[PDB]
Amino acid sequence: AFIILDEVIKVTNRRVNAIEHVIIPRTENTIAYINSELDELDREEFYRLKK
Amino acid sequence: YGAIYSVSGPVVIAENMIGCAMYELVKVGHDNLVGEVIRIDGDKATIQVYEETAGLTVGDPVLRTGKPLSVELGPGLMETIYDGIQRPLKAIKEESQSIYIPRGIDTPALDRTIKWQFTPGKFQVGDHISGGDIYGSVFENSLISSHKILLPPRSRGTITWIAPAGEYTLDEKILEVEFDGKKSDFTLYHTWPVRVPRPVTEKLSADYPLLTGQRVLDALFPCVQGGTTCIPGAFGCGKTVISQSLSKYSNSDAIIYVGCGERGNEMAEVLMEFPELYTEMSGTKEPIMKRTTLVANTSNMPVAAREASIYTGITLAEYFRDQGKNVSMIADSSSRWAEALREISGRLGEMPADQGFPAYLGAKLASFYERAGKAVALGSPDRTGSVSIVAAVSPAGGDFSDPVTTATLGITQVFWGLDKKLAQRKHFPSINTSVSYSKYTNVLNKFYDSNYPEFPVLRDRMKEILSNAEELEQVVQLVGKSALSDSDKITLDVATLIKEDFLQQNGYSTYDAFCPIWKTFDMMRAFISYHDEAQKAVANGANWSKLADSTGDVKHAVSSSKFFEPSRGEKEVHGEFEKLLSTMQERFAE
Amino acid sequence: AVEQGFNVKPRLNYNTVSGVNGPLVILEKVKFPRYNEIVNLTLPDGTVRQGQVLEIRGDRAIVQVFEGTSGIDVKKTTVEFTGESLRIPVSEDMLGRIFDGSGRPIDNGPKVFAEDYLDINGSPINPYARIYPEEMISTGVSAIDTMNSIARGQKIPIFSASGLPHNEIAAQICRQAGLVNFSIVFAAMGVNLETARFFKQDFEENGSLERTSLFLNLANDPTIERIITPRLALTTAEYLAYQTERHVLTILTDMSSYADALREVSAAREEVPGRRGYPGYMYTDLSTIYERAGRVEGRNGSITQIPILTMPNDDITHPIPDLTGYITEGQIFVDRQLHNKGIYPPINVLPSLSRLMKSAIGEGMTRKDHGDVSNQLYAKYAIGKDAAAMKAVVGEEALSIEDKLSLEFLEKFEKTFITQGAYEDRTVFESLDQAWSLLRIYPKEMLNRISPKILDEFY
Amino acid sequence: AVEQGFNVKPRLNYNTVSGVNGPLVILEKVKFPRYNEIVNLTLPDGTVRQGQVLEIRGDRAIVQVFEGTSGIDVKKTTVEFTGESLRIPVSEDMLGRIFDGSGRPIDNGPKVFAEDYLDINGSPINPYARIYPEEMISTGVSAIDTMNSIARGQKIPIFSASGLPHNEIAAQICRQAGLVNFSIVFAAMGVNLETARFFKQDFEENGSLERTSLFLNLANDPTIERIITPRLALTTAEYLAYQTERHVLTILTDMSSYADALREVSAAREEVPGRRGYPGYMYTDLSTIYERAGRVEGRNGSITQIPILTMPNDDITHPIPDLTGYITEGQIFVDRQLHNKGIYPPINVLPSLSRLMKSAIGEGMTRKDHGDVSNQLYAKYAIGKDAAAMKAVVGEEALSIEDKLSLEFLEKFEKTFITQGAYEDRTVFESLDQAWSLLRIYPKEMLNRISPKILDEFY
């Protein structure tokens, strides 16, 4: 039980760190970039409508 | 009698058009092309031609017809196929003897070569007749036994003369109204502006449900006779199965299928299949064409016609409601109707509001969806019609995010949302339980208490099960599902059973083509009783794995409850479901 | 003092219509066009259509006629200039009536016998003449009245989705809400005709119309009328509360529909769409509509607002919820997760808060345990959600006692406290007693957010 | 007998030119201008260029020049109004010839000895005169025939990106397109000379130049003839398929280039843009092009239109692929991810769809199990993609037994079933047998979307 529990704890801690340091930052960066590109498209549409 | 000044696509600017009126049909050019004046500036009236504008030259005469876009309402439109405007495609093909639609074709919307049997109504000479009153009846089809002739609304007076019973055509006089000394001649048909809704005395609250046939739509998100539905456009089999299911079994006295922006061969499919369908509502099987009027508008057709097709269909449905019939007008590609409106706004130069769509898109969609609803048709005798609007919105971005979808959800009562995940699993109908809703549950509680008292609590229980198992499945996909309680395991198992047997159904299958309301209630009884009894057993202390191993037979039985045939009758099937859950209770004792 | 009313000002009938553009009707040779002036357009068919001017120029006025321009003819279209902006005939007898978007009473009753003719726009309230809200206006909704209690004069909107029963919650609040005089003002913008009939029949049947001045604007009703409707409701509220000394509680409905009407009006002019198509001055418009309310110094009356939004894509980042949260003073969230479980009202108390709760929930007001009970309920509901997520991860058995009891509390809370009958009137005291009944499953040692004295006295 | 052909109508040579702007030439004084009229601009250098009248004012005519306006003077340029829309000379011998973007010979052969002059825009086919195709085409590609079937008369485009082998896939489909011989009308809109040479070489090697007509508008060719090339090719196809009763397969390539030409003309006209600058009427133009495919009631003969399209950044949400999906029925999605993995054809069957498959597939037309097998394949491929995403995000062991089996199925599906070498020509029955061999990976229990009778009769 000790060995299995230690292996499972190591896997779970590894996955927690992987999430917090890769998945959350990657998804946050993708969110920021998509929001920036959507703002860029909105600005282009605004300029075209202004013309 | 103005002259063409400018032509640039459908938008035609005609000079000398003084005294014109907005949204008035004008015959543009020498071919007499139909066009509606959509903008006036001085003596120049901007016109959007409803046909192919290529070849129009400056100086071409433009004739003012003096009337808005009017649909010819009367006997003879109950079976025919129409373009965006009320153009009879069959009559056009017969007269032109060609596979093309000639430009400026002036075939009458309702054919005048057919003699219609007429039986005068209770009104006689000298009686006072108001708008919308019935003064006759016409035997159109076996399904439409009495096409009751309505006096046109906003027309009133005293009957100077009424015709006797006999075979009369639409051109022939039927009844005369004196009013203020100016006798008016009324024929079998009449025209009504599509933009202007047909008047009714009072719009009643829709109570009786519209049985779409699909099990999820009928149970979880019910629709009522005279309610907007906003079906998913094409991606899910909800629309494709639902259109034919409604046309066949919805109990609607009439159907007006409106396809705006429909694909070419996708419209050819409807025009070639709907004649083949039959119904068993009468004693003998009769074609659905006797009950359906199609407004066929392919994407090739002009954008103005694409915009006008929705109005034409909804005013045909309004006419059939004013007759006192329950109608279910099916709008195909309301998203394409909205795209047509956006294109027309771009042609006119209007400032788009949201993603190119005009700012008045919400107003137009509201003025369209608001024509629906049960209503007491005006004029004696008292009669209660209804128009259900089963409109489709296409998945523009794959999700309910388009401005047209936003406006439709804002102004609708029922919304059957598309699930991309369920569609990609080929799980049909692909109706997303989380996002879908129906605001008619509260009003339909009366009918449920009258007929199937346990229906609301059962559908609420199934919704609770689905939501709980959706949250639990999110947690499962997160944390591997290594540890789950017996109750949670039962919740996921029951939800998977529901999503595989109850919610999922094959529209083309013989058994599950149309699941009746009593069959759906019995299946909800079976599934909810199974879940509740499993939960009770797990609370007693039984092991879920062993219990599932022992009750695989009962689970297979409640799965085959879907396979139970509906044609056996409500009496026999309910007896089978009574025995199904009778032995189900005893099987859990072990 | 109103003897100036006894005056006849003739109106000019303009047959000069330069052109028609969409909803607009551009006139020419106008004598002295006043901006935002109500105009009675007479069609060639004889139908009379009201209109408003959106632009003014030297001998030119651009009328935005209501109900569209279908049928406007240059040659024969009489246009009559009412020499004033839109005004409503206010009266203390407006209570008990149902009005349209333009102020015309749609109930089968007499025209309101005016006490005065107030401008619909009104004037900004002087901040030096505004008072912080003190007492709560009791709502039958136990969730709102216990966790997100509403003070006399704040603005706390209800954030709901497309299909969630925000209309039903609004009807319940109008039927049950009262003081713990009162005159509810109801404004429905762009509601479906079925919803409007539900509102009317519900109020007439349950007698909530005795104190309600219901303003109904259908979805098919004109968009300019939709713009005018909340101004009408807030002008009625200002009148009643400030020139009559009564508490109002305006309940606006579908401010998303109001913003859509703003979009339609802005694009009727040449205004370029803003962030999400809505005009850049939506902040200003919503600010006016919302901050029309509040308590005042010399007058013993208050106006409360329940804007009730409709979040389009179930997001707060949308401009309507963002600006509404900026101006208003709280949030009440209706949740699809709660709605799909048959819990009515489907209000989740985790995202919902009332920033002015501490003032409303006190000792002289409500009962002295209100604030601590609400804080304890919120903390234990958050713990219940955490334990519900935790059970499917680490098994039911491995949960602590503070997690198992919290799961039991969560079940009882959602299924008995939040779950309220649509016609069940729960006073604040009855709701607090139910809250204490829920909390009593915990031993007194576990309830830590409650003060020791209140815990020893009420448990 | 067309005896009206023997008639001379003198044409008006206008030297009144002005406003020469981009692709657009404006004539100041025109005597009764005709909309959609062809003009012949004679340059000062002497070379003539056809032009189409985009819009007419009272005396103006905004002409778009197909060959471009580079070199068009305002003084010495004479514009001759032909008096009719553009009419391509069509003939039965027109098969087997190579044409320019504007229907001019390229193969160093004579001008088409016209049998009739047909309008480019054609005529609008009566929807009541159309036949639902319901006649599957055995395209020989597994990922198409088995899971997104093509019916003879179906406008099914090939959605692809830049650098993907869409040209190779379309050439393969054209080479092997027997029913379960085809005439071909190929329209090249702005494709590079390498792609045009590839298509011509493949047609010649397969033996298709006996029954094909190429309308090659290369990249170096003028950028406004891309507006006219699809219309010329489609009216050639309409002739060949309706009047000569042939079966025509149209392969309009770079419809994205056509839409770029449309945007270029739309931008020069200074009109209300739409989305991403593409004209608001792009839906109408694309429908006018695409909707010229199908069968007619009287005449046995069809246009199996397959418009190759290129996503600018492999995005369906782009206006060109989105509108093409709206109008054209079905779509064959060529996947950058699949091509990078090395699969040929890199067809992604999740976005790929065919509306007419359900009616042209199964029930004795091809085999009893076609539709159910294709539903099972789609469902299990979606399951495999979801399981691959889950196994990338979280641990592999967390995936269920079904998820692992579906990962194995996805590997054996991309690598064996979809993966099809050029010239392989898999029959639909062989593809179905291979798909079953893929479906025999699973135990019979979890093939849920297979009808039990077919599952028993084919497992």
Image: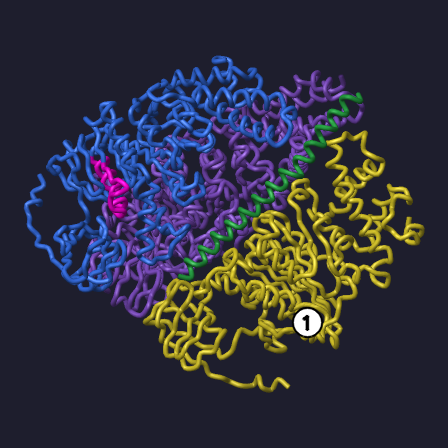
Chain colours: A green, B purple, C yellow, D blue
Q: Quadrant of the N terminus of chain B?
A: bottom left
Q: Quadrant of residue B437?
A: top right
Question: Can residue B128 be seen?
Answer: no
Q: Secondary structure at mark 1?
A: helix
Q: Quadrant of the C terminus of chain B?
A: top right
Residue type pointed to by label 1? Leu
Q: Give residue D71's position: percent from left, percent from top.
A: 20, 55
At a point 34% along the width and 54% down the height, the residue shown is: D267
Residue D238 among those drawn in magenta:
yes
Question: In this image, B524 relative to B365: left or right?
Answer: right
Q: Nearer the viewer, residue B209 or C349?
A: C349
At a point 63% along the width and 43% down the height, the residue shown is: B446
Q: Nearer the viewer, residue C316 or B293?
A: C316
Q: Give residue B177's position: percent from left, percent from top.
A: 35, 60
The prevailing secondary structure element of the residues shown in magenta is: helix
The residue range painted magenta reads: D215-239
